[PDB]
Length: 23
Length: 21
Image 1 (spheres, each protein chain N blue to C red):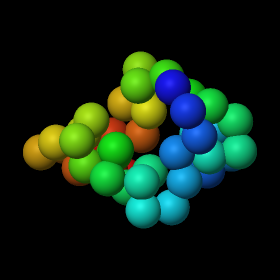
Image 2 (image 1 turned 60 degrees about the vertical axis):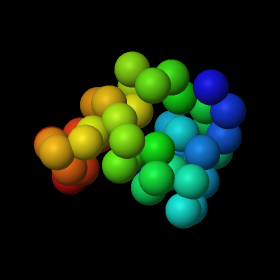
Image 3 (image 1 turned 90 degrees about the vertical axis):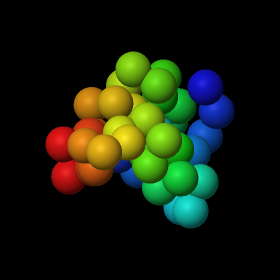
Image 4 (image 1 turned 180 degrees about the vertical axis):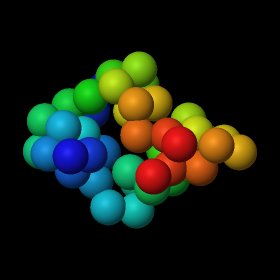
């Protein structure tokens, strides 16, 4: 676990969330 | 919110999954 900012944050949310998406 | 917990601080993948719909 490291700092996740900007574009890297959205990519990590893309993979964690998958088809659910993110609020 | 997500920037405060994950960008300013550090969050696990378990805390990141909290932001999924």
